[PDB]
Image: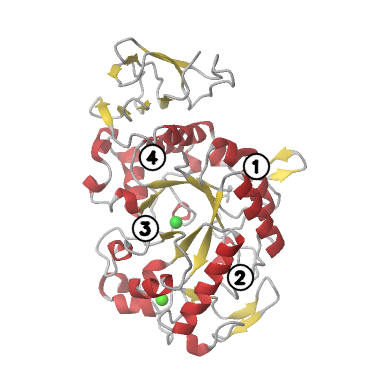
């Protein structure tokens, strides 16, 4: 069962199409969040993608034909496409777009100066005490669209509907906090059917505009999850996570899109140093294992490129699928969605989707935890400096299972490629996990 999606940050359409066929589909990922496919300003920075010029599908990722080809191939492989949609603004200043269109002084090929709110700057203190400025003024000089206008709404809705006709199944509404929830409700009344929609709203508390305001228009990104998870794994006790979710004050599970990190917060935008990223290696492995095994939210695995400390830098000069060579795991694309622990976590979530409860929670009061998903699976994380050798109770059938974080079951189900975990006749497991390691077993990776 599909339960997890992935953000292929800055991946071109050819690399995504191939990735769907060779890896994402066979591994069970549900969908791919692509970078903005519409026309945007020229320049190599990654953020040029967030300054639209028009709604033509000609971007750094490729052209319209390549985009349509990617949707078809991913769809045939059983993987959906979610498009990052800019509903709040257009590009700042003036210049040229990736399809040749010119713009300047709030004048674009599809919008006139009268289609935007009058210019004013959003100050940091506005977030806490002025919802009007937050939703009507400019986010770092980006031309703020008049989202209450029937013309503006029809124009964005027409773009969304065209993407659906091509086969796109979902949308990420970028900068949703800067658009009145009522403007979004009006917009949705113009969108055909009911696609998957998730809204980016950063709400850590004490904001004039809250995340809860967007619960009726679709899913909402729960940024408290990324921040708290990262803070607990780095500075707290894993034992505290026994009631992670609504118990910590997060939004309802069924409404939340969660993650260990995203493209903004791994760069310091909307997240501090406590956010765990690929740079943290095994720490990142363990945090993803927890998120993918824990039954809260709809997770999205991050897929990055090594930016070498340059937070403005665009992606690698080489494609992921380069002449039969895979440019992953080194100083170009990191390909976290391929990391053993992470893909194994996705496999675990997909195979325990019939039991969303946390059963038989166990911990050593600090950094060692273990819990099940009923008789569908069980897992354990050891973040201490000594071996975890406790005997834990499970609801699983006795037998031998592959630790899916370190390998998989063979086609004939007679062997595993990694270590074997034994569930005794009484349902217990005698753990043997080294420092900073983990194990996860599920009912569909049982031997012989
Ligand atoms: Ca706005
Ligand atoms: Cl996001």
Q: Give the labeled residue for mark 2.
A: 40
Other-residue count near label 4 (Cα within 10 Å), few / some / many at <14 / 14–19 / ≥20: many
Q: Tag 2, which secondary structure?
A: loop
Task: Name the residue located 40 percent from the left edge and 67 percent from the top edge.
Answer: 176
For label 4, the SS is helix
Between tags 2 and 1, which lies in front?
Answer: 1
Crowding at mark 2 (Cα within 10 Å: few <14, some 14-19, many 20+): many
Q: CA distance from mark 2 to mark 1?
A: 28 Å
Pick whichever of labels 3 and 4 is earlier in the sequence.
Answer: 3
Residue sticking out furthest to the top: 425
The residues tagged by marks 2 and 3 sit, at their Cα atoms, a distance apart of 25 Å
Disc 1: which residue:
21
Q: Residue furthest bottom?
A: 114
Marker count (numbered): 4
Kindly identify which residue carries mark 3.
220
How packed mark 1 is, by other alpha carbons closer than 10 Å (few <14, some 14-19, many 20 or more), is some
18 in relation to 440, above or below: below
Q: Would residue 63 be seen by someone viewing this image from the given angle?
A: no
* Residue 284 shows up from this direction: yes
Tell me which label, 2 or 3, sits earlier in the chain.
Answer: 2
Callouts 3 and 4 close, C-beta under 8 Å: no
């Amino acid at each position: 069962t599909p339960t997890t999606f992935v953000h292929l940050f800055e991946w071109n359409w050819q690399d995504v199409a191939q990735e769907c066929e060779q890896y994402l589909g066979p591994k069970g990922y549900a969908a791919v969040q692509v970078s903005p496919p519409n026309e945007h300003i020229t320049g190599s920075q990654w953020w040029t993608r967030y300054q639209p010029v028009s709604y033509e599908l000609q971007s750094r990722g490729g052209n319209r034909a390549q985009f349509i080809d990617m949707v078809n191939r991913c769809s045939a492989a059983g993987v959906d496409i979610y498009v990052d949609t800019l509903i709040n603004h257009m590009a700042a200043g003036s210049g040229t777009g990736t399809a040749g269109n010119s713009f300047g002084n709030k004048s674009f090929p599809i919008y006139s100066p009268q289609d935007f709110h009058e210019s004013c700057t959003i100050n940091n203190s506005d977030y806490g005490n002025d919802r009007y400025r937050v939703q009507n003024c400019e986010l770092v000089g980006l031309a703020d669209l008049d989202t209450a206008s029937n013309y503006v709404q029809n124009t964005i809705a027409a773009y969304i509907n065209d993407l659906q006709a091509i086969g796109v199944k979902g949308f990420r509404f970028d900068a949703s906090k800067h658009v009145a929830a009522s403007d979004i409700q009006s917009l949705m009344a113009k969108v055909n059917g009911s696609p998957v929609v998730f809204q980016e709203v950063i709400d850590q508390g004490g904001e004039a505009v809250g995340a809860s305001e967007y619960l009726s228009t679709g899913l909402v990104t729960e940024f408290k999850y990324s921040t708290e998870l990262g803070n607990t794994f780095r500075n707290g006790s894993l034992a505290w996570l026994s009631n992670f979710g609504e118990g910590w004050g997060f939004m309802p599970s069924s409404s939340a899109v969660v993650f260990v990190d995203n493209h903004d917060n791994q760069r310091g935008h909307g997240g501090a140093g406590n956010v765990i990223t690929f740079e943290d290696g095994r720490l990142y492995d363990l945090a993803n294992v927890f998120m993918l095994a824990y039954p809260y939210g709809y997770p999205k695995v991050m897929s990055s490129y090594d930016f070498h400390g340059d937070t403005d830098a665009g992606g690698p000069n080489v494609p992921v699928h380069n002449n039969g060579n895979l440019e992953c795991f080194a100083s170009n694309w990191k390909c976290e969605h391929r990391w053993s622990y992470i893909a194994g976590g996705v496999d675990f979530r997909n195979n325990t989707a019939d039991n969303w409860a946390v059963t038989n929670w166990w911990d050593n009061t600090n950094n060692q935890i273990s819990f099940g998903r009923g008789s569908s699976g069980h897992m354990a994380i050891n973040k201490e400096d000594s071996t975890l050798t406790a005997t834990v109770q499970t609801d699983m059938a006795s037998g031998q299972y592959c630790n899916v974080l370190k390998g998989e079951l063979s086609a004939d189900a007679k062997s595993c490629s990694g270590e074997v975990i034994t569930v005794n006749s009484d349902g217990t497991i005698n753990l043997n996990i080294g420092a900073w390691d983990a194990m996860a077993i599920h009912k569909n990776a049982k031997l012989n």
